[PDB]
Image (tube, coloured by chain):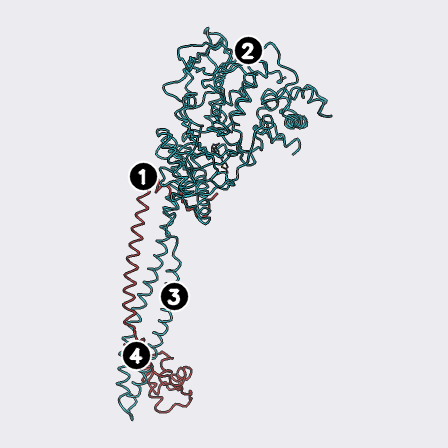
Amino acid sequence: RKPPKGMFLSQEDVEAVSANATAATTVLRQLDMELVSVKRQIQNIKQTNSALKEKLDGGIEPYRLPEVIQKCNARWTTEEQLLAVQAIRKYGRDFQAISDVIGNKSVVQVKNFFVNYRRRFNIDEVLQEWEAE
Amino acid sequence: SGVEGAAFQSRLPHDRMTSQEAACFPDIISGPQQTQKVFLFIRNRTLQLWLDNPKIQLTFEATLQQLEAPYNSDTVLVHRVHSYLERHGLINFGIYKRIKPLPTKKTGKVIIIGSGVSGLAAARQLQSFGMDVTLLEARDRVGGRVATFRKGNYVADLGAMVVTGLGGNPMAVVSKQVNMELAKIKQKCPLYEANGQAVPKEKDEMVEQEFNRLLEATSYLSHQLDFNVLNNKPVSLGQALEVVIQLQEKHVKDEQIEHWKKIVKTQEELKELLNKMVNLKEKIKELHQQYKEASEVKPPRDITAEFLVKSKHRDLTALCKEYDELAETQGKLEEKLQELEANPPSDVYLSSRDRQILDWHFANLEFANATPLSTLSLKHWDQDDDFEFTGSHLTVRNGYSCVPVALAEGLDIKLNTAVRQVRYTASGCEVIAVNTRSTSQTFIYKCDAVLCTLPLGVLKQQPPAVQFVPPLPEWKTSAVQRMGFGNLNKVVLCFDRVFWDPSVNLFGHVGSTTASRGELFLFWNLYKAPILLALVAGEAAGIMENISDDVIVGRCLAILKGIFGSSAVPQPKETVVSRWRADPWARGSYSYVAAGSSGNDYDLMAQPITPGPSIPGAPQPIPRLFFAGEHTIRNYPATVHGALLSGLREAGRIADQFLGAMYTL
Ligand SMILES: Cc1nnc(NC(=O)c2cccc([C@H]3C[C@@H]3NC3CCC3)c2)s1
């Protein structure tokens, strides 16, 4: 039913190498050249990628910031409330960002907070302003 | 083993009747399965009896005595079976002391052309049957293509050497009948390149398996893809080996392409991700600046100023989270690219060194078929491979010449008698022969039938070495051009000191180039005497016949010198170099299934010729011209046993037409 293993005798390939007297060495060098093309291409991106690597030297260690470890509280100080209204104004609804900004209240409180202080801080009016941008 | 062993040893199914036997015994085959089994046993038995002692005639009575009941109840059937076996050379063939001596008065006159093994086999059989046999020989010796060189103790077959296995081989019988020094072949063959350095086991084994894998490939092309005709021409075997090597070479390239195309596909996933990392670092760089500027405003600050420091801090650690995720990913791609660079696929399908060694495997094929692989039929070249005898091929130590010479004991053999014209008519035949030494002395022979064992190369000769009157019908002449008669030659190197490995019978030499793959590519140590024997196969064969013995012998020493060191190669004492295509009594070595030919052409060769009626309106006559020889036996061509079987075959068919076949009632 099928050829010996490793032998790759397609029904369609034989005709292509049998089509003409020099057809064999045609297809065989049509690929000899195509291989070179990819090799050429590999060097290029290997250079381009190598150049980009150099630019990233230093990584971002110098631009890194120490992490704050502050115990989440549950009381809203007048300050924290104010941080909040601004965070909504600049984030809109990204719960994590707003919790990250206050860095003491959490996403549940933050999420709760909109409904608690709702008419009081005009959050709906604020949120429209965020969506404008 | 048993009775059944004798059927196998006679090339016969032990449990079914052959088409042969259906012809002689149609009552049995069309009859009840019980009688068939009786018959079959009677046959299988009788075969046994002959085989266990093949040095004495097996008379019908002898058979009946040893046969037992209930099988020995129907004497006619036993007599019917034994005659059939005897007629067709399955028993009482070869060289045997006969119990009942030859009838003093013979019936019929048969001229046999050629004292080759087919010829003598028929001759012995016909004489055996009470016919008047005479063989006409062009040569001054019998055996034809069984030639043996002899000088002092030096002995080396220029002709056949090998008995291919005794499982079912009539030569098995002959060897018991004539003492034949039958020595086995140790298959181990070490290959030596042009430098004279042996090829290492790694390499030898890896190229041999490719070679077989390559054949297995051509078979697949022929049968499953039906790649048999190309450009309105039959596909040769060699053609399809090119097309298979090319396709395996293409695949090598294909897989290199696909593999590097999988590096570019990843280097470009890296380059695109590097871009994002470089654009994010700049964004981070300027964020930091903004945060520090925002952090520079010392407290106490109003909340919009506090929000800004917190907002910038949150954002910047967010981007520092992206750039960390995007450099874990860069690590994965960097290692993934590293794997791909280390697992590159095979550089080449085969190296120049590798493919030079591959050639030596094609030279072997060329030497087996005595022809360039471009002439072999793809579809049919191995058609005779089912009927291989079992057992390991042997060589004849005292020369193969002894068989032929032993078959000529008691035969009317005119040597130095070159047949030039065969004339065959409704009423009989006459063959015209000259004396080879003085071509003018002319001979006329009359006979009831001619058996022609002229080699196929002789028959192919234009202009004709032998003319037939009337000419052979085209159906015969066409099968003659269609068929292939090829070439291989031998060089016999005779030396006083054995300076090679005496425990290896054969060892190769890898030719420098493909076009010279068969020039002395194989050497044989077969003999008690110190003789190495060099083969010239493929294209080399036809070419080396235009070159001197000395020049040919030189290239022999050279190669031997290279594999053993200039020091240990003494000048050969006696040199003989065959030139079979040149020989006009052979004009070739043996037949091969040419492209465009088939196994049916051998069948064609063996159908005999019936001439036209002398007086128009007379009844359709008897056939008068019969053909034997290795080119007539489709299942066992180009072999001494095939020749022999064809002689046995025609003898029985000639006996049946002129002595009548009484075993059919
Ligand atoms: C181990 C081995 N097993 N067999 C080995 N030798 C051969 O089969 C052989 C060698 C030379 C010539 C012929 C000729 C009878 C062949 N006609 C052609 C080739 C097959 C159809 C056969 S090598």
Which residue is the site of mark 2? Answer: B108
Residue type at the position of mark 4: Trp
| Chain seen in red | A
Residue type at the position of mark 1: Asn
Instruction: Please report, as a chain letter, where disc 2 is located.
Output: B
Task: Measure the C-alpha gap from mark 4 to mark 2.
Answer: 124 Å
In front: B241, or B611? Answer: B241
Q: Quadrant of the C terminus of chain B?
A: top right
Total tally of numbered discs in the picture: 4
In front: B292, or A82? Answer: B292
Q: Are marks 2 and 3 on the same chain?
A: yes
SS at circle 2: loop
| Chain seen in cyan | B
N-terminal label among 1 and 4: 1
The mark lying in front, picked from 4 and 3, is 3
Instruction: Please report, as a chain letter, where disc 1 is located.
Output: A
Which residue is the site of mark 4? Answer: A130
- Please tell me how crowded label 3 is: few (under 14), some (14-19), or many (20+) other residues with Cα within 10 Å: few
Q: Is mark 3 within 8 Å of ligand 1?
A: no
